[PDB]
Image (cartoon, rainbow over all chains, first blue to last red; front, side, top):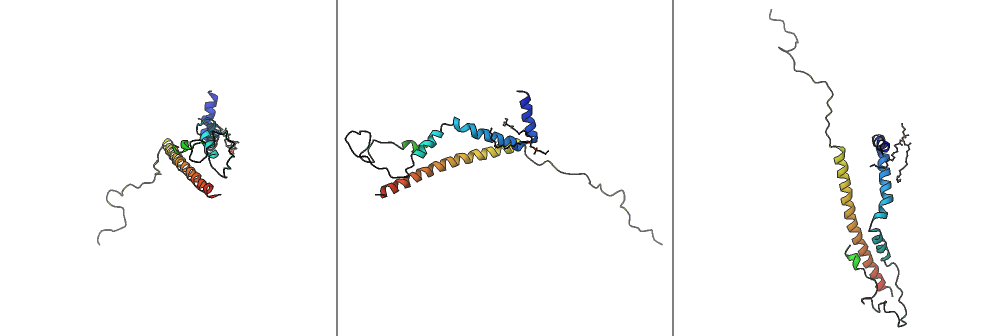
Length: 83
Length: 71
Ligand SMILES: CCCCCCCC/C=C\CCCCCCCC(=O)O[C@H](COC(=O)CCCCCCC/C=C/CCCCCCCC)COP(=O)(O)OCCN
């Protein structure tokens, strides 16, 4: 804890470029695991409709599937408009 | 038979002439420049975040228009 501080000071005095590079790399490595918006990015990626949604045949036993796009059932994007 | 006239230095003496190196300091500290750079980076990051989220919503809208028109 005392020799490494001196090593850090010497590196800052001799190779500032390497100090900055290593700090940036470590931050980029560890920050994404501690961020709450990573799952938000995943959800945004999952919400982009690249292909056509093929409808399902009504067997009369799917209350959770809407019968029209404007019905209350199905997923919602209201979380995205507040972002 | 007038007085001797010759090129000579003026009465008393010529003004002192500078010769030493003169390079003023003329700069801010490193801390200030690093702080300004990091602040600019953070401001840009936040502005880009807003704009990119808006662009994602716009892309979703256009994709939905295509989905409506596909059949
Ligand atoms: C943790 C994530 C890692 C990934 C991020 C980094 C991305 C890429 C960066 C690495 C690229 C390759 C590294 C190159 C290594 C150089 C080796 C070397 O020989 O170093 C000497 C210099 O000596 C040194 O090793 C420099 C000091 C030690 C390395 C630099 C710092 C290491 C890490 C220090 C900071 C750690 C994190 C920052 C914390 C900040 C503290 C608050 C080079 O000088 P010469 O060319 O030989 O000079 C010859 C002319 N006389």
